[PDB]
Image (tube, rainbow, N blue to C red):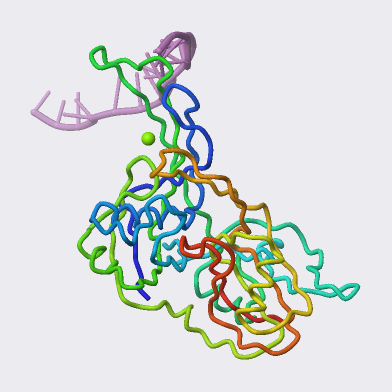
Length: 319
DNA sequence: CCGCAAGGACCGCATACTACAA
Ligand SMILES: [Mg+2]
């Protein structure tokens, strides 16, 4: 597995799906980067390097597989079963009622990010709570710009716009290369355009598997699956897929989640927006009670568009 | 020829203290 590290020179824009044309709708608000955007940046580099075989021009997916992405300062969205109570974010474990897994009422969820070490303790079921100071928020930087007339140096009519950028220190991407020679091509490049407004990020590439993908969790009936990237597909099909890949049937499951992630994007091949897809948002947790004990995998890919970085679930246990 | 050999008042007050288009 190859590990790509993107270091933004300054700011990044991963624009939400909304009109953003000069002289009209003029507000661009960034979201947390979707893995397909990172995949697109890599595919575009290969598209220009002449490796159009691995790109998948006009195709939904490339030949290579983007395992997933993570932002860094490496941090992850607070699991949705972690609820803020006073100055602490408390882990809420599944309960049972009428023979069904439920999450007991303990307050509303508040968004935020935690370090990889805090997530690791969570996945091992050893995390009780997190002090509110260790819960990170992503910094935004709002910039307001204009367009000037060529000669008179005054603002052209209606040419004012606003961008809410993200201030991100690092983005990590992991790629499985079936022999396209991506590691060599990425090594030849120092930087690439990532997201909107022609912002660039420095590129480093190392041949390594992150330790979080190599954890030994043991065997249990009570496994959980933390989605680190958006996961596309019906919950039923995802659970069924999970049953097949682990060769074990499920007694019951509970999806703790939030607002669905709206995913469209821009088709650079056809020069028009991509079709809207809906996904289980990062930070969502699928609690599963298998009928038999399973060896909980450190990570597992689920749902549609796996090669674009979607459906990266991190294994964990609960009691 | 000798001696003395500064002191307090005031102590920045007021007004203006964004306007407008692109
Ligand atoms: Mg632009």
